[PDB]
Length: 102
Length: 109
DNA sequence: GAAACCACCTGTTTG
DNA sequence: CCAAACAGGTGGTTT
Image 1 (tube, rainbow over the protein chains, first blue to last red):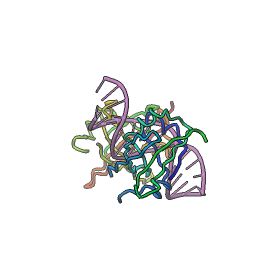
Image 2 (cartoon, helix red, strand yellow):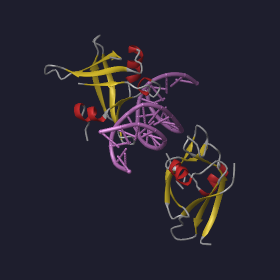
Image 3 (cartoon, protein in one colour):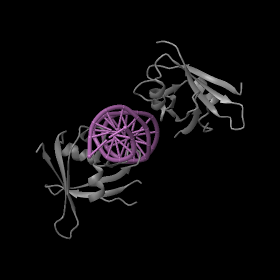
Image 4 (cartoon, rainbow over the protein chains, first blue to last red):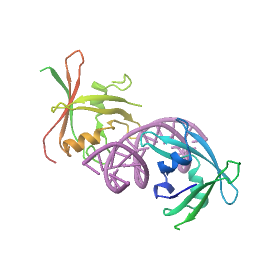
């Protein structure tokens, strides 16, 4: 469960979303590379597959593959908010949803 | 001297610019720095007149078909305040280590 | 070919 | 103050 106000770069041709490292280390641990594949679900019940990775050059956690399709379907914009949630029960499943400028 | 100067270039304004890269003339590039022979790219260690050793990455950018120095060039430019129209002279010592050497000269515009 | 993807790089900003 | 983090970039490769 963490939320980010998305930057212009987040929703542009850079095809990447930067996760703040506090939240990345707290809620999404990485094996310690090419990275892992992560499955989330939106309110429509569609399940999105993203690639979660670490860039050691910039020391930053980023979603790359699959983020742009999310941006385009949801018509994300700079200033909107993206909220990551997890299952209440043992299903262990992650959910993604988006609100707009509080 | 103990040093042999290899080549020099009067820096374009983009060499000191936000592009953070020094275009190296292909004529002068294939001559002393052959990239297939590794002189992806390679890291080169060049020492200045102040004694500071500077590490740059030397590669060939197919997009511009340019031989270029790219990583650390901005630091050199910022510390030396390299400006468009100044000159960069690359040199090599005739020693067993054959160390490479760099420093800049003055001239306007 | 175009768009996305990939692994690097850096200048500002800031606790 | 300054190392860290990150918003904004690059060239090259795969889809």
